Amino acid sequence: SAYGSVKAYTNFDAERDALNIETAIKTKGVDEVTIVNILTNRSNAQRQDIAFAYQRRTKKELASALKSALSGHLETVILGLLKTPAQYDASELKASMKGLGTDEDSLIEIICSRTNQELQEINRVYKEMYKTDLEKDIISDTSGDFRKLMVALAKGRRAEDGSVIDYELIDQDARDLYDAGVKRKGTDVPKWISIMTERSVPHLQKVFDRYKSYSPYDMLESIRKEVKGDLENAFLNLVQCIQNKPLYFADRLYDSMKGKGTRDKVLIRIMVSRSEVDMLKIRSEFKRKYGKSLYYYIQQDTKGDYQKALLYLCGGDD
Ligand SMILES: [Ca+2]
Ligand SMILES: [Ca+2]
Image 1: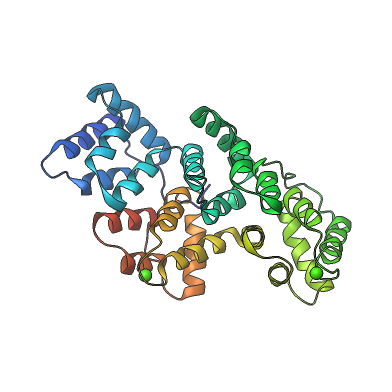
Image 2: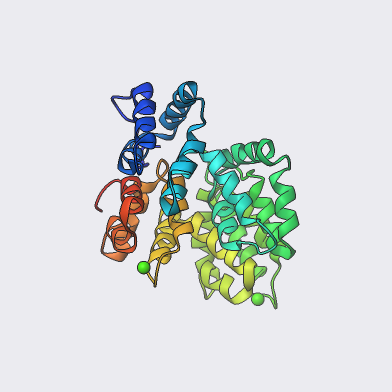
């Protein structure tokens, strides 16, 4: 993707990077800025190479030494940046299901936003890591139609974005979602789940637009009237991700910062997991909607080497 904010380092020397990181870790009080300076400016692939080189000579896992050396929010950023995308998501997903007190917000964010390709690797990696399938763990922590929705999405088997646009199916899908929701008493949720999980994203974009032709309310408002709870939250997030994924993340970023304090879990995860996907488009949507940059809000809400790390993931003012 040409829309990430963290690009590969041109002058990449994987051994110099490991050596310098060890020097920085060992020194008194820890040289965080150097640790940050390197990793936030190396691609994930490049951090894998820094990782391999570093273990080849310290006897230690880079992640372990860093988990030791660093603390607080900055620890969370750095250890998340070290994992591959597939591994980072698998572990956030596992933490969302943690205990009985489920973090529906995080589960929803990831499952709703990840592509077929990403979920192929996410499902794979989750098994090797936790010795259970992702689907099994989702079934265990969620129920009702919320579970059905979450499970179907996690299979990552959306139709691929075809060559031919199927306008007949776009129109029928729009009526079907009308007929299953605002037209009828209550809701036919499995029609919603089927349509919204199986069709290509470019297709559903056109469906939700054509849906405005049949329904007094757009899809987002229709969801709000038809359902509630996790199910409603899931659908709302999903329709946002389909319509404008970058805006979706921009809005979640705004939300994590707009009020008192910071929702650091959401902020850190968005900045880490989207840095090499669409952070540029996220930054662009953010600035357009909110009049000020992402960079600026991060700066107001966070401090220290934590703040510097995040700003580097952001990659520019505006
Ligand atoms: Ca209804
Ligand atoms: Ca704030």
